[PDB]
Amino acid sequence: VSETFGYRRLEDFMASHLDYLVLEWLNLQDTEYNLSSFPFILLNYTNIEDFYRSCYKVLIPHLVIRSHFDEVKSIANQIQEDWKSLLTDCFPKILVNILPYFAYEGTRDSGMAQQRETATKVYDMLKSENLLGKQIDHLFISNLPEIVVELLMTLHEPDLDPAPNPPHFPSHVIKATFAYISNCHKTKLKSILEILSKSPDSYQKILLAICEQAAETNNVYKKHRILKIYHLFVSLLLKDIKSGLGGAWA
Amino acid sequence: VRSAAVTCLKNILATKTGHSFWEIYKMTTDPMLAYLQPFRTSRKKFLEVPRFDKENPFEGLDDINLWIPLSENHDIWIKTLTCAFLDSGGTKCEILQLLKPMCEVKTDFCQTVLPYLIHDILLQDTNESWRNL
Image (cartoon, rainbow over the protein chains, first blue to last red):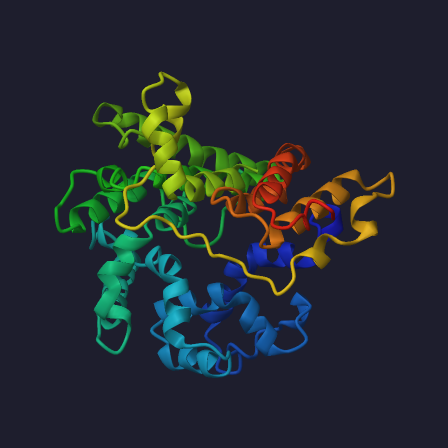
């Protein structure tokens, strides 16, 4: 099936849907179906250690959003790496499962609610001194661009169009998350692009990131989704052109 | 190619030589000034390119197979020759050592940059060793 679809190797094809696979496996909530019980033989991984070292960027965010810290500490202790580094590498992937729930009309739906306070609790225990909460503000303000890239990657508008990876939100939720991020800043800038203008080169990175996605996929539907994300980002850039993007307009 | 170009532009503009170049080039009315403005940054300390010190630099280039290609691997031959020239500590120019990532993605860039590498190495040559080789 992988060579039929045009993927160079089965690993890329399986890692495309690994997010959905892991989420459904965890939601199935069977005691016998633990993280180690997940079949990694389909991923050409001979042992679980290589599977962890290859897909940690996906595994840790899902455990963190379900408040499973002893599992991630384990994966750290048999991964031959510090758990702080593993937590700080996948910070935007954890964030995209937390920030959008805060800014979108809470208490309207029961499921969206329980999601929004469960993300609230996750953020609160993340702020603890033992975890990375001591320097979470510096990390948030340091590397913004791929946070924006990851959040924009979740765009999906609900017509026989296959859905993306399970974490996906509409455009207005994304704009509300941008506004919430802007207001959360100490200076409280009106828009996120104002604090993005403090580093004029950052915009370029974001653009390149989107283009990189268009490079890695040959599927028409995925290409159309990336085009929609690019259109949304370019429109957002064009909206506030008068202020100037820190001299990076040309 | 675009990512490598952005990285090279940032690294070059982060050095003292880039600042000196900009100080004169800012007078000119050129679209390149507007295009390269975002990548220009103000920092207290200029970027310090590491000084590579080999025990012997000549044996890296002293190879007959390295110079004469096989008539079907021109791209590989020129890339290997440029990479061998850059790897050794012969060069002293600040901006040249920052051009390695871009040389690995384009053959035309290697062809363009090789004469400058040779000129820089020969300029600082002592007791006619690099010249003879």
